[PDB]
Image 1: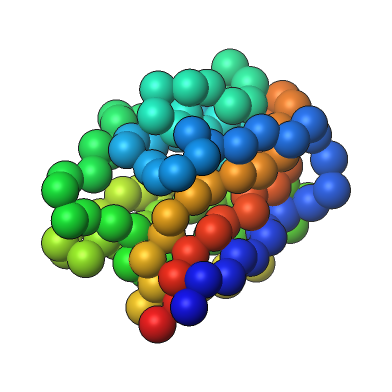
Image 2 (image 1 turned 60 degrees about the vertical axis):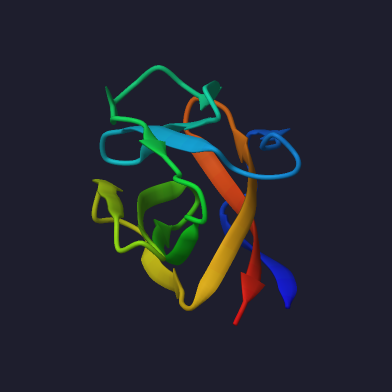
Length: 125
């Protein structure tokens, strides 16, 4: 069943993922998530360090995700259905929330200098 969940604060300007799906993800992070790079498109600032890009294989998707957040996105980590891991990247602030047994289909959000928020569209199993 398809649903969505917002994480983080109220600031920044809105962005969207590609629209249908999600082919690759990288982040910039320090103490917080500075940026999320979705399908090669940058959303957020130029601070922090750039992660390697995670590129989803055929039949591969985000299945479990842990996000630390307060007013911003502090940390992102995920696992896929193929057992691959991304992160954790970011700091230790905020509070943790986990999507468990999902299939993420799109990531939208809001950003300025940092990644303020994410709105994750996923199938909840």
